[PDB]
Image 1 (spheres, rainbow, N blue to C red):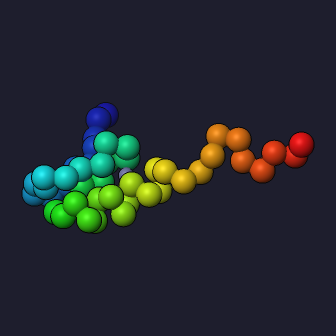
Image 2: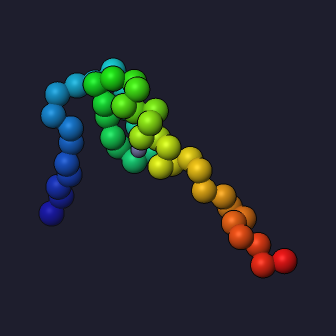
Length: 46
Ligand SMILES: [Zn+2]
């Protein structure tokens, strides 16, 4: 079988990291935050 979800309508802005679109650009940039913040190192135990 093969299935997949997709947004309803169309937006000028879209997130190419997870797949979340937003009518406005202010609703996208504030969302991409979840894709930017962590660190590849983290709390190093010396
Ligand atoms: Zn996203």
